[PDB]
Image: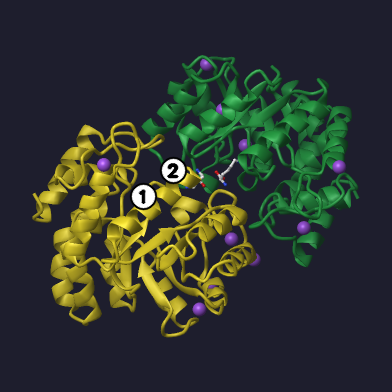
Chain colours: A yellow, B green
Amino acid sequence: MFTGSIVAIVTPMDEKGNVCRASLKKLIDYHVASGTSAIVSVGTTGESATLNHDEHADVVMMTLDLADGRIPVIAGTGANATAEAISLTQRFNDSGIVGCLTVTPYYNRPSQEGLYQHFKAIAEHTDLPQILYNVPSRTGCDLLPETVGRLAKVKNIIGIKEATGNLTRVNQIKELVSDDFVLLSGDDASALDFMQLGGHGVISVTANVAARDMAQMCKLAAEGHFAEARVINQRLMPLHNKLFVEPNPIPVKWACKELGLVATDTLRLPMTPITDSGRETVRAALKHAGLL
Amino acid sequence: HMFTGSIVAIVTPMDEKGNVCRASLKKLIDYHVASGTSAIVSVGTTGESATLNHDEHADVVMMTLDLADGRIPVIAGTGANATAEAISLTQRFNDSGIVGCLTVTPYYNRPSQEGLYQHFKAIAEHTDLPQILYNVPSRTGCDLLPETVGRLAKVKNIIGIKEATGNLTRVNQIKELVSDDFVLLSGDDASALDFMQLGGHGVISVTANVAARDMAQMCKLAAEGHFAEARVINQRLMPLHNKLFVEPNPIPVKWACKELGLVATDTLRLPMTPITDSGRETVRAALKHAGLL
Ligand SMILES: N[C@@H](CCCC[NH3+])C(=O)O
Ligand SMILES: N[C@@H](CCCC[NH3+])C(=O)O
Ligand code: NA
Ligand code: NA
Ligand code: NA
Ligand code: NA
Ligand code: NA
Ligand code: NA
Ligand code: NA
Ligand code: NA
Ligand code: NA
Ligand code: NA
């Protein structure tokens, strides 16, 4: 259930910056039809930083409601204060979400022991499966394999979204955890490599606009058909890269709009609209992918 | 002028349950008044801004302002990674008595230079208070470049920057793009004296929590061009400048304050955790090197 192509879904907005349900419905219908394994709601790509606690909870519950049992929903529950993370987590207990994605605290740079006590306290206040999430380029801290191994012994700590793009982390973690600990890439451009080394899937921004390809690529990787997966990956590589040509989710929201998947590409400050150059680049990447 | 010299990034002292401890904060503020500290930054990074909710944050700022009682200026930490949050935090301290705001680049969501421009511009437009930008890429994932600083210096109440890269070339890259009354403050204790000798006007300092008079003298000596004497102080303090980050700030400086008798307990809020045995030994030796123990 926590394997294959998982979309880190955008939070579509109207021109005032409020959540646009009609657009989110369209995306969720698109992912059900495309074979996406699951939806991560209000991750980084979903602009977690700029939704307040109640808007955040509302978007997750909206996503769950619209999913209507057709596709599993994983809630973004990360926070850089352990009390905030527990409170967010408790908000979704017994909601119908199948698990949580909880990022290492950002900006206050805790120690490895700080991360251990942080994630352990979170896990002790829920029954939901917990997927750790490491992305040092955003957070200023690096959850190391040693610490992941300590945390994997905690009951409902069940996997990790590893977004460093450092592919040596795959088997560094795998040798410290049990066979059913889930290893998920959080870096689209290196995700097929990550799977070929033993990863079980990807929590993906590219899947927002290339869901069918991403789902088939990940299934082929799972079946060991890496040559066939790489043909898809190469079609998608310009998107993997150029969806970060400006701060995510600025490009992917523009791309969703360009494809008719959402009504507007509006974001909340401090995100700002895509530049002329960025549109040109993302459009070429979408054309390279065969989507335009 | 008011934003020069030694400015303490003051800890938020807590009791054993993690609640703000007014009695320890009062002692610290009296200590800074007697030590000649130029100003207090309230609820910055060293003050555990992340783990105080909006009401606790505002309460700590108002407490610090009340305890200072006009004896020393107070600068409120008002940064946020959502612009709406930053405006709302800023609006809370309008006409409170604080003299200015310290506002960090959005963290975790990694905005562009244009996003930083619009962020800080929108903030400045919702306040009459002086704004001090704060760049610390090692924490935020985001680097406010001098060109963008120069753009923002043209917004009238954006009046300075706390530059915490430790990259000393930024001093004059910024200074040549701004007017001469734009304030340049180090946010990196180990390189602060270097920063001032290159033209910086002061430092927003963690070391000043426990070596306030030394830090006040070092900055005043630097300001008067007495760099040889300032360097003597800096070498007394350099192990502290470094070892107060031997573990995540403010874990070492809070333990040092407790060991010096300045606060009652060294308690923090998760995901900060208590100082290790090795860390205590390292920080004690640095305190002894400064002559403080
Ligand atoms: N802007 C803050 C608050 C988040 C509120 C819940 N989405 C942060 O990024 O941590
Ligand atoms: N923990 C969140 C919310 C802070 C609330 C105000 N001190 C952050 O660091 O941005
Ligand atoms: Na709607
Ligand atoms: Na660490
Ligand atoms: Na540690
Ligand atoms: Na390790
Ligand atoms: Na487990
Ligand atoms: Na008290
Ligand atoms: Na402000
Ligand atoms: Na100005
Ligand atoms: Na400096
Ligand atoms: Na401690």
Residue A222 position in % (x across, y down):
25, 79
Q: Nearer the viewer, residue A287 or B154?
A: A287
Residue A53 position in % (x across, y down):
50, 46
Circle 2 residue: A51
Residue plotted at (29% across, 32% down): A15
Q: Which quadrant would the N terminus of chain B be assigned to in this image?
A: top right
User: In the figure, B37 relative to A261: above or below?
Assistant: above
Do the numbered discs 1 and 2 sit on residues whose CB atoms are within 8 Å? Answer: yes
> How would you rate the neighbour count of disc 2 (Cα within 10 Å): few for under 14, some for 14-19, many for 20 or more?
many
What label sits on residue B166 in the rendered view?
A: none
Q: What chain does badge 1 belong to? A: A
Residue plotted at (51% across, 21% down): B124
Q: Is mark 1 within 8 Å of ligand 1?
A: no
The three-letter amino acid code for the residue at tag 2 is: Leu
Q: What chain does badge 2 belong to? A: A
User: In the figure, B61 relative to A196: above or below?
Assistant: above
If the picture is divided into quarters, which one holds ligand 2?
A: top right
Q: Nearer the viewer, residue A292 or A262?
A: A262
Residue A160 position in % (x across, y down):
44, 69
Residue plotted at (46% across, 16% down): B154
How far apart marks 1 and 2 lie (CA) works out to 9 Å
Q: Nearer the viewer, residue B225 or B83?
A: B83
Q: Is mark 2 within 8 Å of ligand 1?
A: yes
The three-letter amino acid code for the residue at tag 1 is: Gly
Residue B54 position in % (x across, y down):
61, 39
Circle 1 residue: A46
Q: Earlier in the sequence, mark 1 or mark 2?
A: 1
- Total marks shown come to 2
The picture quadrant where one finds residue B215 is top right
